[PDB]
Amino acid sequence: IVGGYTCGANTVPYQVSLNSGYHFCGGSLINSQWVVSAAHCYKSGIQVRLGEDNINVVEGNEQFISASKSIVHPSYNSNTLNNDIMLIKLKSAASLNSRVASISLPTSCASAGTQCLISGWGNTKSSGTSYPDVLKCLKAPILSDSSCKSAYPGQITSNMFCAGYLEGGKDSCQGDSGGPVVCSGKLQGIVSWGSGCAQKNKPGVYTKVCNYVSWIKQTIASN
Ligand SMILES: [Ca+2]
């Protein structure tokens, strides 16, 4: 997250870190046994880390649970990033409390102008590299589809939205991928892609979760 603020420990209780020996992507806990992340974060050997603030220090609220099954969306396209969503099933259920909690799925899509919270452990610089140990947060609005398509001609599908600031300076970045965009207490986006970080006229692009609720629910019910 570029241009954000330190969230505070366990203030984003649905945020998870995906770990394969190191943090590589975020995700969101949607019930006690399932996480949603970006398909471009797929790999084998994932441990899900719940209850984290500092990802390099054991602080006492963590739960570390291995994945048993990962399911990339059936229509994910790695070239265009269309349908950039996956589900991860945990080997055992997490223990839910005030510091480790699920986030609700949306019943309707959010409109442009809605303010959302984006969070992650990604790079904090737009030029150069500095990775934080503690969770960072950013409040940002959803942008109109027309603005989004103007910024990225030919690249925005109906399964994507832009959020952020056309003036630059505040954005998600490398290492934030897969993490949550929460608006009015519902999961509306997944950190997906952009051109650089925090550049003028190049806001972040997010997977539009409201288009996937049916697939999520039916997949969980059967797996
Ligand atoms: Ca920790």
Image (cartoon, rainbow, N blue to C red):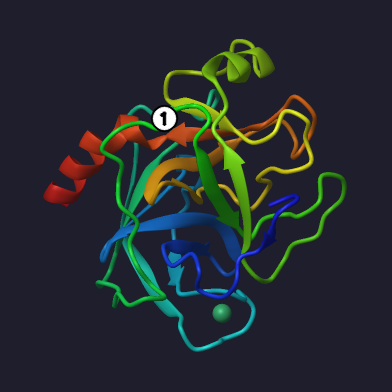
Residue 70 locus on image (x, y percent)? 34, 51
Question: Measuring 46% from the left and 44% from the top, which residue is drawn there?
Answer: 38
Residue 86: percent from the left, percent from the top?
A: 38, 44
Q: In what element is the residue under mark 1?
A: loop
In the drawing, does residue 197 fall left or right of residue 140?
right
User: For mark 1, does the 10 Å Cα neighbourhood hold few (<14), some (14 to 19), or many (20 or more) residues?
Assistant: many
Asked if 31 appears above or below 213 in the picture, the reply is below
| Residue at 51% from the left image edge and 64% from the top image edge | 17
Give the answer, above or below, for where 5 lies relative to 154: below
Q: Is residue 125 above or below residue 165?
A: below
Q: Which residue is mark 1?
A: 83
Q: Measured from the top left, where is residue 213 in percent x and y?
A: 26, 37
Q: Height in image: 200 above or below 47?
A: above
In this rendering, the count of numbered labels is 1
Tell me if 58 is positioned left or right of 160 in this view: right
Residue at 76% x, 55% y is: 124
Residue found farthest to the left: 222
- Give residue 46's quadrant in the image: bottom left
Q: Amino acid at mark 1?
A: Asn
Residue 72 percent across, percent down from the top left: 36, 41
Q: Is the C-beta of the residue carrying label 1 under 8 Å from the nearest atom of ligand 1?
A: no
Nearer to the camera, 194 or 74:
194
Ligand 1, by image quadrant, is bottom right
Residue located 26% across and 64% down the image? 33
